[PDB]
Length: 70
Length: 328
RNA sequence: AAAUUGUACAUA
Ligand SMILES: [Zn+2]
Ligand SMILES: [Zn+2]
Image (cartoon, rainbow over all chains, first blue to last red):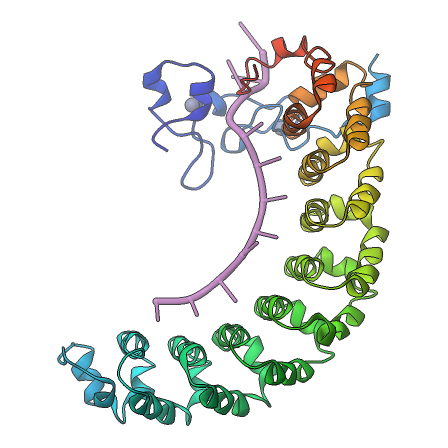
């Protein structure tokens, strides 16, 4: 939509915000800031790149897991 | 094409009237501009011309209904015609309602008829389609028809479907088209028809919420069913709020659970999410789905839980500012 | 610093 949300919520300068979109006409990833990032969980990069909270392997956290982490 | 359709597809008759369409409506209803013209100029004049159009198409009804453009014609007739024509059409349709419901345009027309015809002929069509419930609900076109019937017919006549569902309510509440049929069932039936299906649902509640279609069934029972069913489902979640607010489908079920509830249920669940081991609150505010549960909890709670919650996760706010969440 | 907030409902 004529601008990239990621670079906007990341408070990049306004020129960068309106200089690209987040994803693609092919539904790849377009934002270079997000394409540079390698996922520490699933290694994916570039075309399928994503941040940690939205990673497809971000594991379901149970109660007992929340107890062990203490 | 013949002569007249090549004359009108180029538009050479700016003052055309219904009577001018003689001996070419079968070909006009198969052309776009012609079906639009016949469709839009069938509200004025007398019924004599409308009787003509009825006669010239009662010979090709079985094809105009399975026609991409004729189906609007058949529809408009079922909507605007004198009851004699309603019955005269209604007659020759029986004997093929299976096929005519499986086909796109024919089933559009079938739907269009069930809102204007007589109840008796309606029930004739009802008794027509017994048993095939399987192959019909599990179809891209049969399910829409089924829904229109659930909206327009007497529940007691349809009760046989209530008996074709036992042993199948699960594999259909999880079906992409069946789930809509089940929602229509629950929103348009009696106590004695919802009761067995509602028990069937309360059986497979667990696996249903984590399914991308059963969760619409649950969500539909939570904001439309009786308070009792609401409580019955509300209790079968206590102990799993953290595990489910992380699930993509079940999280909406959590939201629609905290919205519709009594003071004891709301307070009970708020208490469940108050005893979370600090880092599980971090899972809440952080995870992509739970935070919705968090906010819908912030908006609907009583002020006691409010002030006993604005503080409960007030530190994690600092770790939430760098997101998109502007929460005062 | 890893920040984008989330699932269904058919004919020119
Ligand atoms: Zn960007
Ligand atoms: Zn990943």
